[PDB]
Image (cartoon, rainbow, N blue to C red; front, side, top):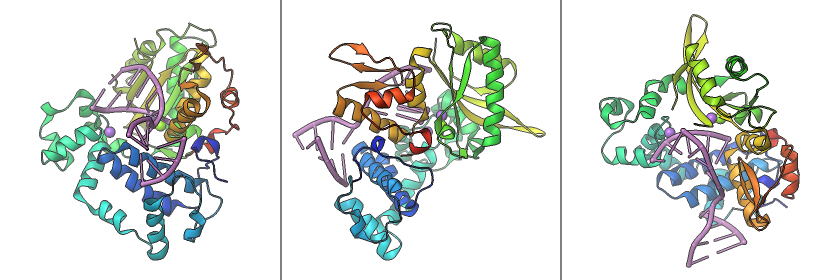
Length: 327
DNA sequence: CGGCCTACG
DNA sequence: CGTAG
DNA sequence: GCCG
Ligand SMILES: [Mg+2]
Ligand code: NA
Ligand code: NA
């Protein structure tokens, strides 16, 4: 009844099993901190299955037959239903390792492998990292410098202000170029931790060289605190606020218009949705999907898509609008 | 047994 | 390695 | 951890 791939089922933003999914996602995150991407994926997938259910799970029997629920994920739900807590989840939550790995990997520029090395070296707090700055990349220095602001929710009012200044810079750099809001905000989220924009031009080839021109124009307006030929720019903007400013993470992506449906699909997410869609494409349909195109490795050809709907159709999938891709 | 998404900076 | 969805 |  419940399809096994997340791209085969609608997942709305608001759902009925948040307590259960959040517990499984703690175990997924902890699996990642220990270097087990496979266990992370299973727990992510199991959490996502619960997000797609039409009603609250109140009895363990409601799990029978569900994909990605085996002995371990079922026991977690069982304990939560019977007792309101899962001992394993609580042990993880309270552990110094989990808390510190979460603290460090939430820094922009720091992933699991870097966080784990620092943990093994005895580091535990952000001030510990600040006390040893030669051990930081430029990206990490920027992540730590702006960490307070980057932990503040980005609101819709911020998104609208950012879209205006990005549209102004893009228009100065290339008349006729367009700016599309992607990421979680396109899926209907009201808050986020960053803002994602996709930039193109209707005439194929005119977007060559656009992103450096856009960045130069934003920097000369004093809008850029941090950035790295290129097509993805991971920025920190100086966003004006009444009497002051705050740092905000902004991603700017350029795509030629021939690739725009693929980039729009990829950058709209969710992350799990897109991993599942790429897995489905290759494993079930024998086609290779990324944010540039959909490749048939037998014919050695690329699928010409005019819309996201075209891509779903070519993959034999029922179309899902962005607000149902919240896997 | 062995895969688990697939890119760019 | 980091980043992204 | 789950499954093809
Ligand atoms: Mg985002
Ligand atoms: Na990080
Ligand atoms: Na982003």
